[PDB]
Amino acid sequence: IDLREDTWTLQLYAQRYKGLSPKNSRELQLRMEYDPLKPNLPTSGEEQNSKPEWLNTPPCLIPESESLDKAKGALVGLAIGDAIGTTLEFLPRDKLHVNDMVGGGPFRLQPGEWTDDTSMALCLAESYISAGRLDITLFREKLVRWYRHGENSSNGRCFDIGNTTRNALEQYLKHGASWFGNTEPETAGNAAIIRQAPTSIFRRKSLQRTFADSDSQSMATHCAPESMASCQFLGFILNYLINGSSREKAFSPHVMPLPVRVLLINAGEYKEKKRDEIRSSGYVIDTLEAAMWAVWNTDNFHDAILLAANLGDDADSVAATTGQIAGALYGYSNIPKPWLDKLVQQERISNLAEQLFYMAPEEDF
Amino acid sequence: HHHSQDPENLYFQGQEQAKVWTQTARANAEKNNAQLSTLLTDDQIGAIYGYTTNEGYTALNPALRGQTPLTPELEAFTGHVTDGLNKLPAYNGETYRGTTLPAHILEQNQIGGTVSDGGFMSTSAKTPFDGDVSISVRGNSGKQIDFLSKYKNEAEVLYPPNTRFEVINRIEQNGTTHLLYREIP
Image (cartoon, rainbow over all chains, first blue to last red):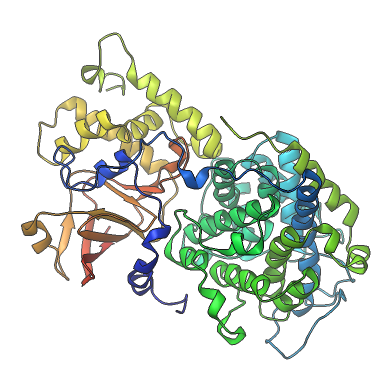
């Protein structure tokens, strides 16, 4: 099943995964009745204010310090994937290969210099540490300082900003804190999933706050529903991994509300795909599916990063996304030590992950 | 006409249920998407939230759909919801409404036909589980309102009264009649 098919075709196909949808509440069900005073539909739903089981956070069964290793893995792994994949950004698959942190790429980078993936992630992480919550205006201001003056860049300048992200900061500069836009499907690019790890670290104790912060962080620049929901799905994957679930548990299907292309990723369709059926474009659905695929088809952090980067095309974004998942799965301590050395600002990035990890608020009750 | 002046008659004379809706909806929005909250006045956010309560919905949508009288009070309630909806960013994609229609209504849903409901139309981004009919809806007058709920869990995308849709696809698969609605603005 080709994720680029039309959503009418995908939706008819996806009926086989009706089971992955949470049931309506009693009240949403009434709102879907032809006649709410004369209900027709099953009336077994739970109350609208009640916590559904798919938001019940699994208690962390690994040691806290193992979770900490995985939280550091998620954020440092993002930057690692970023710095390796940039080498092949824009290149045709299999025309060139990368298998070490060598820099180069379109922006002629030194080894270990990361790009817009990590810069945006750092802005997001810093805004959490400052405000103690997702603060979209503060996050945008930090993004503005990165874009306009090179704050939080690996080499002093903003050099690789995505078009959708650029328009959002331009629109925010022009219209102020109440602006939202980039709602059209053209704008369903990578930039919000490639910066996701800090939200998952900060909300590691609350699936519901992960769900609420993940689409919100995306809307800072990207309001396409496929971007928002891809952040929620990745954020859930990171949560399960940071809290110690095996790859099998985390990559099995989860009950959660998702639009059909993200739902099909949740359902595991990539598990059956060959490399030449996996796309690595800047479309958020392609990127997310390729990252999941790269992690499912490798056994260690090193190999997951190299499989993703060597997909070519938007190799940068797929490796940064794979870096988040694989870093959460295998842990900071299993990232190759030579890569940590070359990675620019590696200590600062690991300490931000650690700070987010310890600041993580308690689950709501 | 104030939001409080609009459901005053739907509730006990003491209680100021518009203020209660607004407070809960503000608290939910603060937790779930604080910046979206700043786009809405007290009456906008309280009205949308009220639409999602049982007593609110069953007073509003049956009146707009012609089953009960559409009083000036219910009219101002409607107007506050839509004023709020007009501020939110567009949901541009596909959402679903799982429902069971009387046969003579399903009969009117043919490819090439047009649909326009006087009430609000609730949809959800999630694939629907129940209903003889699954209505896929593409448009972009519909707005995501889950951030006003407690758990942000149901992905409700709300379409305002008198949104017109063309029926652009239809098929029965397993036991279920699928319809495709495209908003015609």
